[PDB]
Image (tube, rainbow, N blue to C red):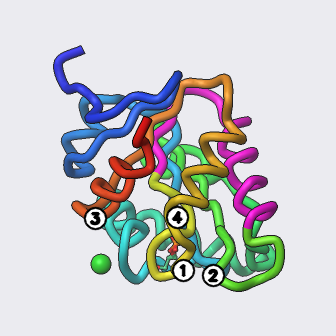
Amino acid sequence: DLILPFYKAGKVSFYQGDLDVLINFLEPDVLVNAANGDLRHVGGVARAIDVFTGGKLTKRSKEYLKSSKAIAPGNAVLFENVLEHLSVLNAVGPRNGDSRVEGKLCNVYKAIAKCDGKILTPLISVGIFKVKLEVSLQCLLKTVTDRDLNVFVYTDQERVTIENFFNG
Ligand SMILES: O=P(O)(O)OC[C@@H](O)CO
Ligand SMILES: [Cl-]
């Protein structure tokens, strides 16, 4: 109620604050990570998420990668209870100029959609992966059509660009 998304489109809400406050206020069950393929969270949003978990995310990721194949853009694996009652799914998105940049992204959002509970997710493969926002948003917006979802908006730019993208 008393922290309001700066924009709501359908069942989808957009919040730009810092991660602690938001996660604390929204009480999500799954937090989505804009992930590597090899789960190295060295900057951007995945860095934040990791710190947020006191690095427990990284810890789990390494282990994960010693009995499991790296992650193909277009997919996601969920780590349950990374912190108590908080799960992270690492969704790897496409880098700008792979094949089916679009159909990959879509699957990601599709995976994100199937998760149970309240979700908070950054906009996918839109940072150092360099896919333009219009596309990711468009994918997400198009793919997850009937589900409450909370997009974490990570920077002032992400914000402006999202503003434009809703020009009515
Ligand atoms: O997928 P994006 O959002 O572009 O970021 C990749 C990131 O995991 C590198 O640290
Ligand atoms: Cl950064």
The answer to whether mark 3 is within 8 Å of ligand 2 is: no
Mark 2 or 1: the one toward you: 2
- In x, y percent, where is residue 153? 34, 52
Q: Are marks 2 and 1 in contact (CB under 8 Å)?
A: yes
Q: Tag 2's secondary structure? A: loop
The quadrant where residue 96 appears: bottom right
Residue highlighted by disc 1: 129
Q: Give the total number of marks visible in the rendering.
A: 4
Q: CA distance from mark 4 to mark 2?
A: 14 Å
Residue kind at label 4, given as amino acid type: Ala
Residue range highlighted in magenta: 102-121
Please tell me the numbered disc located at residue 157. Answer: 3
Q: Tag 4's secondary structure? A: strand
Give whichever of discs 2 and 1 has the lower sequence position. Answer: 2
Q: CA distance from mark 1 to mark 4?
A: 10 Å
Give whichever of discs 3 and 4 has the lower sequence position. Answer: 4
- In x, y percent, where is residue 113? 68, 37
